[PDB]
Image (tube, coloured by chain):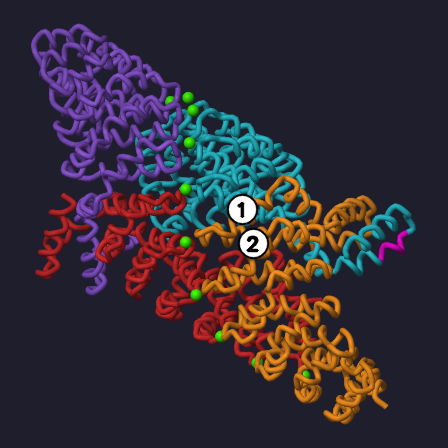
Chain colours: A red, B purple, C orange, D cyan
């Protein structure tokens, strides 16, 4: 009954087309067996292609359906990605249309709560620089949604976190730690906390950005939700490096570095000597 | 990110090898400086105040944070001490909140893993009586954290080892040599070993407390790991006076020692010789 | 997939499976208003209203969302929100530079204004109309759509409510949205203007005097069926007035446009198109 | 290599069982890529068996390993489940060893953080009655981990939420809304908040358990995490009923009801008739 709804995404009519989209849009809302049902009927290419509709009613509906398909299994996120949604999503990040801009951020956020494979895709697709740009928005709804999306990215592996750092996000995050808007403060603390829970390098970048005095100050907050997030972030700062040191020691590092003691490249040699000195 | 990095230390790809090395050298420097930055930015006084918080959720985060700060070098541990943390930590040893009691013990355990100035501070804050009471906990999670901490204390000098003996830890530690839990058995053994590593009134009181028959009997354990610790302990005792050798003579040690020579475990065959040599 | 699978076991052959499926649908059909009433009876509204003055954006937003949910109940539930004193704070939040807070308050106001006339009139009496009207020229499509939705609920009341909307200067801005390239705003504008056009001859006349007809008439040539439908409904409403009203739609040239619709594939169209051309002879 | 490590997991040689155990737990503690290597080798089945071992060092290692793997993607979780872990993990809830008990819980809570069929495998294995009993534990560590697990379960579809209700969870959740312990209280709010985000019947159970007066008291809390969590739950109670009424309307419920006036059974006609009236 359902590849019928699909072919009608191609329909000359807009009551028909939007009957179809409205239908497919609610079905996508009902959990993973239903999402896959939409997927297998081949809905993704149609829905991606409507991302360029000049009709905002078609556009926001398609956008909303992709976001919902993106809110299921990693495997279902991967299908959105495979359909080529990312490049389009990234362009919509420039919409002067606040409501389209928010739907696309939300969609990206959802994709970015996937595995590190789908986070890397979002990163490869060029999304970090627009997200960071948006950290300056005077619209607190877009700002919140951007912080969130960045938060999920910063919840991947260390290279994911490092991309976020390398895209320039930290100075903004640290200024928002002074914000008198508790909702924004807390989403920026949340994202910053994710950064702080990578390894040595990631922790160092947070420290070099001047987060610590701002975090120490938040420990006077009568707001226990913000106090808890400042303390959790601080405890990551204080633990991450030694825990990484010990995990590389566990992963084979002494041996590896001894073998390189005698490297024939001299620069690699001194550096390997230097690094064994450190894992003492 | 870590097994990758280590395998890349052997990579025939030169830029791959080199950047992997650079990362690994940074991770090798550890976290102590990052911890210091936390101290320098003023976090200690607030963490210490929060240790009297009646909010369990906050108090846990604060304890964890301090515990990690105490996972640093002796400088960072000493800073937690001079911040006034110890009185409240020793208080928390009476908490009926198992989640708070475990973090406090852990934290105390890191402090106790510094040098003897740091161990002495923990003794002098009165940690020992509680820690001894905890050796008879039916709660293995709590028992083992207490054993851990006691062990670190008992790895200090003879004044540290005596404080422990004086606090009445030996009977408890000995009862635990009858434990059918191998994780507790091993740690009780390690702690006994550290005690027997002291001078001669130290080696004596351990003998005095009836350790040897359990010790000897453990040599027959077919679990090489618990065998080692028991050997090592009996070897530390062997190392002592003459009344002391005569004491390990008397508890039927020679029979058991005699077999361990053929052991494919290189280490065990060394120590096992050392000890028989030592009697006479 | 609990709900589609439920809707299928009603057509099912098995009697047990039909039975219990129906038993669940029935409870679900009864909706959430008694559950909203229980939240009210346990004493939540006074703290919820207090939280509206809160410096904490996080707490304020959640409160706003709770209130708006409570107000998404029946008229009894809306009236309890009103009586607990929420409107002054809601109307206050209409000036807020915070878009997030602004949207929740518009939304909350929107739900209050989907009640009966007594509920709508309370919103009107709290002074919400001038800010709603000013927000119809916001460059923010999210804020604008929410203010349009609210005003349309308000204009879906009695003539006294419709006239309040008119008296607050809504029409110039509603007409100007008739030129929007944004289909979603255009449809809501048409709908609001359709409601206003569904009151008395003097309300209909104010719509004409505001210049709606020229835009309305063009919208009849729209390739967009959904836009074309709302345009027709509104024009239809206007056609449903006294002689002077019928003349003005004659004199904006609605007749040619309305004939070029009798031959239309679409369904709700020709019947309405017909009834419209009918009303002018 | 990895393939004879698996073979040695079922060796009689106790020593190389444990080297083979430790190594597998090492590599399987970093990244999803390594987890899979461990999986495809065939570690899972053997690892499940070691959950029977009377050696704690062995038991806890196996268990912690499974724990780590269960903290990957839904299909990694699924592979733990396919391996047969659940009946063992559920049994381990009866352990008098607190460390084992907590590790069994944490493992269960990770598995239960997957998609809905994973959550459902956990219900199916009979975890709910054990989880519900734990809600009376005087151990706050065990108590909190049980609530977290039940929280994860209640984050599935209404059928999963209903299975937490049917198992008797609500009266303890309700009582814990009075707890002066903020960590326990917050975790119960979260669980209850997940329950209340379900359908008309799920909200009705929460109402009938007398949640509302306590949730309403919480609106006076000076703790903004708690206050926010009480607003949220109350918000879900106020919306889920109407939102589900509309969701069934979209699911075609009207054609189906009208169709039932055509039943030969008056009861059915009457109910369908009462239903169609109500759906306005
Ligand atoms: Ca068309
Ligand atoms: Ca357009
Ligand atoms: Ca703003
Ligand atoms: Ca507070
Ligand atoms: Ca026990
Ligand atoms: Ca504020
Ligand atoms: Ca705009
Ligand atoms: Ca045992
Ligand atoms: Ca307790
Ligand atoms: Ca408390």
Viewer-proximal residue among D217 and B4: D217
Q: Kindly identify the residue that appears in the image at 24 percent across and 43 percent down.
A: B43
Q: Position of residue C164 (x, y in %)?
A: 67, 70
Do the residues at discs 1 and 2 belong to one chain?
Answer: no
Quarter containing the N terminus of chain A: bottom right
Q: Which residue is mark 1?
A: D231
Residue D154's image quarter?
A: top right
Tell me the chief SS of the magenta region: helix
Viewer-proximal residue among A38 and C274: C274
Camera sees residue C62: yes
Decide: marks 1, 2 in contact (CB < 8 A)?
yes
Q: If the picture is divided into quarters, which one holds ligand 4?
A: top left
Q: Kindly identify the residue that appears in the image at 48 percent across and 60 percent down.
A: A110
Q: Position of residue B64 (x, y in %)?
A: 31, 37
**Residue B214 in magenta stretch:** no
Residue C131's image quarter?
A: bottom right
Q: Kindly identify the residue that appears in the image at 70 percent across and 81 percent down.
A: C207
Chain letter of the residue carrying label 1: D
Magenta segment boundaries in residue numbering: D259-263
**Residue D260 in magenta stretch:** yes
Left/right placement of residue B156 relative to residue A81 reads left
Q: Kindly identify the residue that appears in the image at 57 percent across and 63 percent down.
A: C106
Left/right placement of residue B214 relative to residue A276 reads right
Q: Position of residue D190 (x, y in %)?
A: 51, 42
Left/right placement of residue A160 relative to residue D245 reads left
């Amino acid at each position: 009954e359902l590849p019928q709804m699909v072919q009608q995404l191609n329909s000359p009519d807009q009551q028909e087309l939007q009957s179809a989209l409205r239908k497919l849009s609610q079905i996508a809302s009902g959990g993973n067996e239903q999402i896959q049902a939409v997927i297998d009927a081949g809905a993704l290419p149609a829905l991606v292609q409507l991302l360029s509709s000049p009709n905002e009613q078609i556009l926001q509906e398609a956008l909303w359906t992709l976001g919902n398909i993106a809110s299921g299994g990693n495997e279902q996120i991967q299908a959105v990605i495979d359909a080529g949604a990312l490049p389009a999503l990234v362009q919509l990040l420039s919409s002067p249309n606040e409501q389209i801009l928010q739907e696309a951020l939300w969609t990206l956020g959802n994709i970015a709560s996937g595995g590190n494979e789908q986070i890397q895709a979002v990163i490869d697709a060029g999304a970090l620089p627009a997200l960071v740009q948006l950290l300056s928005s005077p619209n607190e709804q877009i700002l919140q949604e951007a912080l969130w999306t960045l938060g999920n990215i910063a919840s991947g592996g260390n290279e994911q976190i490092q991309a976020v750092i390398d895209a320039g996000a930290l100075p903004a995050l640290v200024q928002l730690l002074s914000s008198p808007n508790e909702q924004i403060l807390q989403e920026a603390l949340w994202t910053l906390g994710n950064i702080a829970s990578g390894g040595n390098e990631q922790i160092q970048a947070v420290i070099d950005a001047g987060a610590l005095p701002a975090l120490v100050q938040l420990l006077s907050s009568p707001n226990e939700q913000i106090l808890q997030e400042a303390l959790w972030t601080l405890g990551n700062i204080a633990s991450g490096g030694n825990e990484q040191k010990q995990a590389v020691k566990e992963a084979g590092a002494e041996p590896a570095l001894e073998q390189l003691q005698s490297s024939p490249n001299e620069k690699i040699q001194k550096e390997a000597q230097e690094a064994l000195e450190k894992i003492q």
